[PDB]
């Protein structure tokens, strides 16, 4: 427990140091909105084919009957610009809605519980997630579980003790060269093959790969 | 000096047969980077660590340790 | 069949709206902001298409090579694994799909080549297949391990509520059924593609409409912009020229909006395919009717032109 | 439920967890062999 707590604290410090060294997802949308806003302000500096950019100049030097075509041209140019801006904002809003739905599902599953789906709440086996406040967004501290050190083992899918095939309930039969043990698929916990963790299903003449092993049978010593 | 690739003509950077990771993409499976003086080099991107997993019908791997890693999304 | 990417294109204004005349560029300065918007949108679309391939195929940073031992307990992997007879890395199935699914650069509508080539996509699929048949799910969730395929299939059987004693007792039957199913899907796939052929046909239709709009007068007295300049004089033909530019700009904006909607749909499909890969391929998804109709065991991704298929 | 052997599995020694208590196990096979 102390080792896992120290590893979690070291990971928290590591991501705190790494995040202090910019953000990609949050800074992109702000930059796009700023660019769209700047383009909207700079649109009125053009003429759109007319003889003037500002309506005041053309309305002053020319009468509104003469300025009718120029005012209409500016009106339709600004309408086209506003329609393009609205379409771009609608596409961006659809993208943000999809991202917010994804983040809401992530908060529902990985934060409010342990999601059984892999590669959805961080790489590796997910344990928990810690949401943090962000400007115009949210981040998740996906506390995952990955293996570090492994060893090569010899495996047997079944054990024939007294003419009957034995299969592990949760573990797997592994060997280090001389003896055989059962352990889980995510950690090395060698245990003596017994009746409690193995069940008998048929005979041992139906499997292609098998080894000649024995069962401790813990009921037997306590009978004496 | 002048290099001809699938994605056009690339000048100002030499071509190296060695394959490394892709930092600045160019196109058609070729990227460029500022490596070793030092100059820009164009090369085919590496697809990852070329390793072969030893597979056998009676060989398994069971991990004995773990690291609690936190990933920020 | 789930498409993950489409054809990348780059369209400018001086090559499409304008031709070989200088006054077109002078009148295009008043609409240069619109062309900047369209160029930025096309660049973002190309970047999005380049990124979509990375989120689907590049799920592992380590390349896994198939061992020379082909004894997988009776499971035949000849169709999904690459063959050494063909110099290309495409699997037999991939080779069938490459030929199953089928210039427009005349007017400046150039096509940007993808960052990841088809050979690299096939290599990614082969690496994923090698990782799946040797580790099952540990290569996609941390350090890669080793496991026999019989034990991996027994593990996949345990994830749907069936104990492992029904697997080894009839392992030959399961292997024969898997080989027969692979042969059946190989025979059925040779008879076309629905989702993959739709996006290519849509892009071709959009490009054809783009080059066809240049032959429309848009209410003017001529279709091409050179005839009015050669026959009429500049100051009285400026209205016809401006009408041509605004018609071409409307057509280009409509094309850009349609391509943006198609790119959003392509991104949604690519996200769906990436989630399918991450759950069904790199592990065993517990979601019912997500990786196929029935109890899912495993999936084998195969490279496709501008897409990916899944053999659940 | 009464704490028995069927629902409890043993692993490791006793001086490994900071929080532990003293209790007894019914051992449901002991009265059957009498
Ligand atoms: C494989 O693991 C077993 C279990 O620890 C080892 O067997 C024990 O070895 C120690 C000394 O090495 C003995 O004191 C024990 O009596 C052994 N246990 C039994 C049940 O006999 C075995 O040595 C290991 N094999 C190798 C090659 O290291
Ligand atoms: C495991 O032990 C059994 C029993 O000792 C072996 O079964 C015998 O195998 C020999 C030759 O392989 C036969 O001549 C006997 O008739 C078998 N006896 C029985 C009762 O089946 C078995 O071969 C051993 N396993 C391995 C892999 O050698
Ligand atoms: C599993 O990995 C952890 C982390 O690398 C190991 O903990 C280290 O152990 C060494 C020696 O015991 C210490 O000097 C380090 O300070 C420890 N690091 C941390 C972060 O606690 C642990 O020993 C490994 N376990 C096994 C069985 O190898
Ligand atoms: C795996 O399936 C392939 C089918 O693609 C088998 O290859 C065939 O083998 C037969 C037997 O000689 C030949 O007549 C066919 O011409 C082969 N077809 C092809 C396309 O090569 C292959 O033998 C199977 N492997 C195993 C181990 O069953
Ligand atoms: C739980 O039981 C253990 C052992 O029965 C107790 O440990 C003993 O504590 C006394 C006084 O603290 C010592 O004199 C003994 O030497 C200890 N024995 C052993 C084997 O460690 C423990 O104190 C009990 N816990 C509680 C809360 O009563
Ligand atoms: C297992 O064996 C293979 C080759 O036999 C080797 O490459 C690998 O490093 C070994 N694993 C360990 C944990 O030593
Ligand atoms: C593993 O395959 C080899 C090669 O065919 C074979 O000699 C060996 O007996 C097999 N082992 C098991 C346990 O099936
Ligand atoms: C719980 O925490 C308190 C506060 O320090 C401490 O006094 C107590 O011993 C702890 N109990 C256990 C079982 O850890």
Image (cartoon, coloured by chain):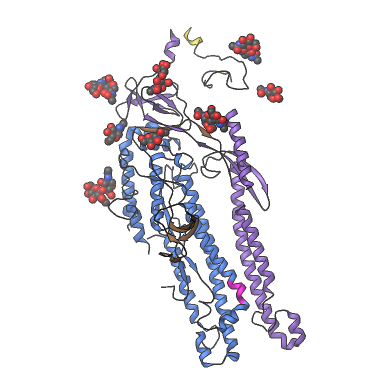
Chain colours: A purple, B brown, C blue, D yellow
Query: Looking at the rendering, which quadrant does residue C147 occupy?
Result: top left
Magenta part of the chain: C31-35
Main secondary structure found in the magenta portion: helix
Residue closest to the eye, C136 or C154: C136
- Residue D7 seen by the camera: yes
Q: Is residue A208 above or below residue A213?
A: below
The quadrant the N terminus of chain A occupies is: top right
Query: Looking at the rendering, which quadrant does residue A203 occupy?
Result: top left
Furthest residue to the right? A60
**Ligand 3 found in image quarter:** top right
Residue A220 in magenta? no
Residue A68, x across and y down, in percent: 71, 85
Q: Is residue A216 above or below residue B72?
A: above
Apparent side of residue A120 relative to residue A112 in the rendered image (left or right): left
Furthest residue to the front? B37
Query: Looking at the rendering, which quadrant does residue A174 occupy?
Result: top left
Residue C302, x across and y down, in percent: 39, 52
Q: Residue at x 58, y 73 (%)?
A: C35
Apparent side of residue A167 relative to residue A117 in the rendered image (left or right): left
Q: Is residue A3 above or below residue B69?
A: above
Residue C307, x across and y down, in percent: 43, 57
The quadrant the C terminus of chain A occupies is: top left
Residue closest to the eye, B55 or A70: B55
> How many numbered discs sit on the rendered protein?
0
Residue C220, x across and y down, in percent: 55, 86
């Amino acid at each position: 427990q102390k080792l896992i707590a120290n590893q979690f604290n070291s990971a928290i410090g590591k991501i705190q140091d790494s995040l202090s060294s910019a953000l990609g997802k949050l800074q992109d949308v702000v930059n796009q909105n700023a660019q769209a806003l700047n383009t909207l302000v700079k649109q009125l500096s053009s003429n759109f084919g007319a003889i003037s950019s500002v309506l005041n100049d053309i309305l002053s030097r020319l009468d509104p009957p003469e300025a009718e075509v120029q005012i209409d041209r500016l009106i339709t140019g600004r309408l086209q610009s506003l329609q393009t801006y609205v379409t771009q904002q609608l596409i961006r809003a659809a993208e943000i809605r999809a991202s917010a739905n994804l983040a809401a599902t992530k908060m529902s599953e990985c934060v409010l519980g342990q999601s059984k789906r892999v590669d959805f709440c961080g790489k590796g086996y997910h344990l928990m997630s810690f949401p943090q406040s962000a400007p115009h967004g949210v981040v998740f501290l996906h506390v995952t579980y990955v293996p570090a050190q492994e060893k090569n083992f010899t495996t047997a899918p079944a054990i024939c003790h007294d003419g009957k095939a034995h299969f592990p309930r949760e573990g797997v039969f592994v060997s280090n060269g001389t003896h055989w043990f059962v352990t889980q698929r995510n950690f090395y916990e060698p245990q003596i093959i017994t009746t409690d963790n193995t069940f008998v299903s048929g005979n041992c003449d139906v499997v292609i790969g098998i080894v000649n092993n024995t069962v401790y049978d813990p009921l037997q010593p306590e009978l004496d | 000096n002048v290099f001809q690739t699938r994605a056009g003509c690339l000048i100002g950077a030499e071509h190296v047969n060695n394959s490394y990771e892709c930092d600045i993409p160019i196109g058609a499976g070729i990227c460029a980077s500022y490596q070793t003086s030092q100059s820009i080099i164009a090369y085919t991107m590496s697809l990852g660590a070329e390793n072969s997993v030893a597979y056998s019908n009676n060989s398994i791997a069971i991990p004995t340790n773990f690291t609690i890693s936190v990933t920020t999304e | 069949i789930l498409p993950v990417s489409m054809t990348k294109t780059s369209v400018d204004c001086t090559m499409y709206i304008c031709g070989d005349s200088t006054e077109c560029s002078n009148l295009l300065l008043q609409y240069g902001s619109f062309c900047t918007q369209l160029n930025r949108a096309l660049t973002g679309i190309a970047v999005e298409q380049d990124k979509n391939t990375q989120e689907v195929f590049a799920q592992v940073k380590q390349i896994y090579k198939t061992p020379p031992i082909k004894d997988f307990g009776g499971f035949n992997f000849s169709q999904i694994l690459p063959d050494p007879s063909k110099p290309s890395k495409r699997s037999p199935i991939e080779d069938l799909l490459f030929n199953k699914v089928t210039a427009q650069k005349f007017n400046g509508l150039t096509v940007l080549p993808p960052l990841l080539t088809d050979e690299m996509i096939a290599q990614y699929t082969s690496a994923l297949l090698a990782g799946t048949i040797t580790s099952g799910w540990t290569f996609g969730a941390g350090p890669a391990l080793q496991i026999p395929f019989p034990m991996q299939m027994a593990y996949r059987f345990n994830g749907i509520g069936v104990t492992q004693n029904v697997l080894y007792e009839n392992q030959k039957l399961i292997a024969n059924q898997f080989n027969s199913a692979i042969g059946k899907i190989q025979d059925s796939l040779s008879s076309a593609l629905g989702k993959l052929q739709d996006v290519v046909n849509q892009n071709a239709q959009a490009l054809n409409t783009l080059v066809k709009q240049l032959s429309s007068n848009f209410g003017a007295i001529s279709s091409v912009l050179n005839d009015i300049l050669s026959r009429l004089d500049p100051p009285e033909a400026e209205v016809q020229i401006d009408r041509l530019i605004t018609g071409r700009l409307q057509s280009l904006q409509t094309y850009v909006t349609q391509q943006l909607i198609r790119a959003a749909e392509i991104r949604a499909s690519a996200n769906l395919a990436a989630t399918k890969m991450s759950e069904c391929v790199l592990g065993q998804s517990k979601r019912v009717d997500f990786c196929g109709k029935g109890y899912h065991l495993m999936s084998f991704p195969q490279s496709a032109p501008h897409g990916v298929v899944f053999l659940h």
